[PDB]
Every structure is written in C-alpha cells, then in structure tokens.
Length: 288
Length: 53
Image (cartoon, rainbow over all chains, first blue to last red; front, side, top):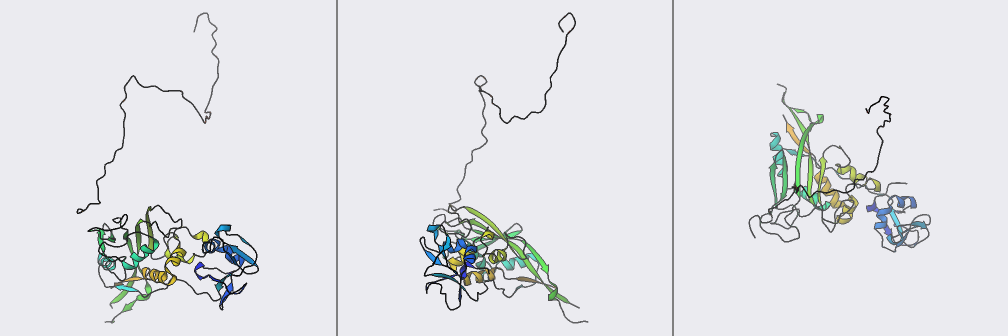
C-alpha cells in the first residue's frame, strides 16, 4: 500500500474494473485510509467500484465498503506527482539597523501584505481589505504597535455588508536573526568580511470566520472570533507549522487545526501552493 | 452617518450587594452529603463521692 492524496483521485466510468491510460484501480485497503474524503466526494445514493471485487457506498449508506461490482471505478495516477510546496529565491534587505529592516519588510506590497492577505482570505477570514477597494489586501494600513507591527484594512467612510467594520488583522512579532556559515565573503587582504543572516518571525491572524465556509476542521457555522499563530521559520510545533500540516493531509487522524484539502478543493492545487510558496519565501539581511 | 459611528459606548452592571433588614432572615433545613469520618472518641465519667461533681 502507498499513501493516497484525495486531490489525485479520479472517478472513471469507462467500464467495470477499467481505469484510464496512466491510472491504477484504488484498493479496498487504500480506500479505507481516506474513507471520509471519498465518501464526501460522492452523491447520497451513489455506489462505485474498487479493485478485487469491492464497492464503496455514499453517505446515504454511511460509507460502507462491501463486496460487489459496479460500472464506475475510483482510480489513482500510475505515476503520482509530488504536491510539495516549492522554494523560491531569497529576498535580501538592504543593510540597516534592526528596526529599519523590519520597516522595509512590512511595507512591501508584492512580497508581503498581499501574499499574507490572500492566505487569510483562503483560510476563511472575513473582510480582508479596506473600504476604498473591492480586492483583497488592496487598501491596507500599517502601524507600529509596541514591539510589533499591525496590518489591517482602512475603515474610513461607509461600507455595505453584514458586520462590515469588523476587519481581520495581521500582526507580525517576535523577530529573530540566525547566521549561516556558507555566506562568507571577503575583499582584499591588505580584511573586510561579509555575511547574511536569515530572519524569522511570528504571524498572527485575528478575526471572525465566514458563515458560508471556512477551513477550520470542525467548520463552525456561527461566525465566531478566532486567533491563530504561525512561525515563519524553522519547525517548532505541529500547531504552528504550515509545511508539516500540508504534508500530513493524507492521514485523516492528524488533521486537527486546518483542513487544507478543503482549500485545495475550493481554489485549486496550483494556486494554493504558489501562494504558500510566496508566504514562506526566505528573507536575508546583510552584515559587515 | 458620523465620523466614528460604530464605536458605541457600553454600560456595564456588576458586583451586586444586599443590605438586609435584621428581622427578616430565615433559613430552612440543613442537609449533608458525601460524609467521610475523621475521628471519634468514647469514654466514661465516674463519680464515687457523696456529692454531685
């Protein structure tokens, strides 16, 4: 048996026990591993075929797997593609003091604010943007709050929408700088050295979740308030690691904070991984 | 319509206290549950003289 990712499954209707060109029939054991996802991707009274004379039934039957035969068949690609989040080239901040580096980081629109505002929107937060535009993360304001920074939509003038006025906030805090030994460089030897250090921080999202649909695993439906934190840097915990949670989306019992399969279904695989790649882009600062 | 209409003032009521009339208090029966013994003692008091003691 091999791990199965719900986004790769394909339901063929060619013939009994026949898959596509590059496609293998899903096994009864493999179907059991992701039972809830496949049952959620089926109609109420639908029955579909598996390998070795087995059948999966829809929610009306409580998702029972029993011996049988059917015309349809769930198939998995014969050569699955890796859905891992790609890595982008580093972003280098011009030399300066600690607070200057943070200021230049948090005021960048293409490499920040907009990649961070789209993540919050995809996760299901409400009203990510200001009153003077219709697009997410367009009319935003940045303020220095204590030892951190706060980004949120501008709220001047009026707005149309239920509870428009409660705008979600992005809070950046807890910066740290770790030096790597492979960036060493020197000039003449009459010497002046040079290094680059990687920057890490904590990102907090605060706001209320949308009623129509959100990405929390319990899928609350009463518009509750919510605060969550991510660590943009080396792994520290399962709850605050994006890469970890995304890589264990094939184990249903590991899903306890966010449901990334839901986001993939809602928006598509390529867009989600591009956005996550932009959010996790490395950041470096020079030292001399 | 207004500059910051939407930031509305809130009034909070808490910390209630009661000043009783002295001759109006009554209570009913006292009941016990979940009883666990601590200690007990028994004894005798003996008087062998000719007067109460």
